[PDB]
Amino acid sequence: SNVPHKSSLPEGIRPGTVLAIRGLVPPNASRFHVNLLCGEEQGSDAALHFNPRLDTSEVVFNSKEQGSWGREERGPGVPFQRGQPFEVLIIASDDGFKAVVGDAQYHHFRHRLPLARVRLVEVGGDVQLDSVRIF
Amino acid sequence: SNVPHKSSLPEGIRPGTVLAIRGLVPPNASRFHVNLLCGEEQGSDAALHFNPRLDTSEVVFNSKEQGSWGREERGPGVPFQRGQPFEVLIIASDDGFKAVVGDAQYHHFRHRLPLARVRLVEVGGDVQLDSVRIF
C-alpha cells in the first residue's frame, strides 16, 4: 500500500514547492497523515503535520518544535471519505502551507518553523497511496 | 474565433503561486502558448512565454520586454501529443518558474523580469482549454 512512504529532501524545499499526494482512503480507514519533518529520527520536529481523521470527521494541522506539539488548527470539515480517492496539494509559500483538496482551496497554515529545516516528507496511516510527487 | 483566454491576477503572483492548466491539444494542432503578462495593454511585457510547438516538435520558453523577445530556452522534447489531453503546472518560485507536464517537472525558467510585475495569465493558440486555476 506504499505506506509508510518517505521522500528525502537533501536541499530542503523552497517557497514555491508543490507536494502532490494522490491515493485512496480505504473502506475502514481511521486517519492518515502527511508530515514535513526536520530529520529522520523517531519523533522528529515537524514543520507541518497534516492529519485527516476519518473517524472523527476532522482535519488537524499542527507543528512539533523541540519535541513539543503546537496548538492544533482545524480545517473546515473533512474533504475526504472512506472508499473514495483523493488528490491533495500541499503548497509551500514564503508565508505558510496552502492545502488544496479536490482542486479547491481548503486551508492555509502559517509557518511556525523555518521552511529551511524541512528535510523529509512522510506519508502514513490508513491510506493506500497512489503517488507522492514533489515539484 | 479562437480568442485567447485571459485571467487577471488581482494580487499579482509571488513564490508559492501555482498556475494549473488542464486541456487538450486538437487533432490538427500547430502550437499553443501560455503567457504571464505584466499588463492588459497589447504588447505588454511577458515575464514568461510558454510555447509548445507540435509542428516543429519543440517547446520554446522566452520573455518579452519593450516589444523585443529575449533568449529562447527549449525543453527536452515535447510532452504534448495532438489529440491528447494534458495537465500543466506553472509554479512560481524564488529563482524562476517550474513547468510541470504530466507527472514530471519539464523545465525551470529562471526569472528574467520581476515576479511582482505579473498581473495577467493568457492562453491562446491551438488548444482546447478545460480549466485554468490559480492556487
Image: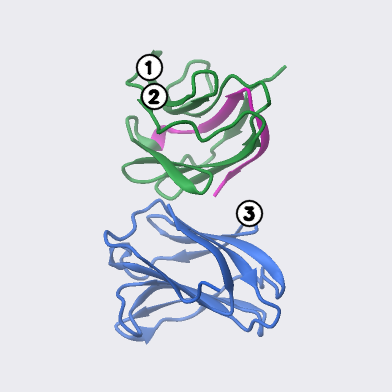
Chain colours: A blue, B green
- Indicate yes or no whether the magenta region holds residue B118: yes
**Residue B134 - label:** none
Circle 3 residue: A103
* Label 2–label 1 contact, CB within 8 A: yes
What span is colored magenta in the figure? B116-135
Q: Quadrant of residue B130?
A: top right
Distance between mark 2 and mark 3 Cα atoms: 29 Å
Horizontal and vertical percent for residue A109?
47, 66
Q: Amino acid at mark 1?
A: Trp
Q: Residue at x 51, y 76 (%)?
A: A33
Residue lying furthest top: B67
- Under circle 1, the secondary element is strand
Horizontal and vertical percent for residue B77?
44, 31
Q: Residue at x 60, y 39 (%)?
A: B86
- Under circle 3, the secondary element is loop
Horizontal and vertical percent for residue A110?
43, 65
Q: Residue at x 45, y 33 (%)?
A: B118
Circle 1 residue: B69
* Mark sitting earlier along the chain (2/1): 2
Distance between mark 1 and mark 3 Cα atoms: 34 Å
**Closer to us: B67 or B9:** B67
Q: Amino acid at mark 3?
A: Asp
Mark 1 surroundings: few (<14), some (14-19) or many (≥20) residues within 10 A: few
Q: Is residue A115 left or right of residue A57?
A: left
Q: Main secondary structure of the magenta part?
A: strand
* Label 2–label 3 contact, CB within 8 A: no
Distance between mark 2 and mark 1 Cα atoms: 6 Å
Say whether residue B66 is visible.
no
**Residue B63 - label:** 2
Q: Residue at x 34, y 85 (%)?
A: A42
* Label 1–label 3 contact, CB within 8 A: no
- Indicate yes or no whether the magenta region holds residue B19: no
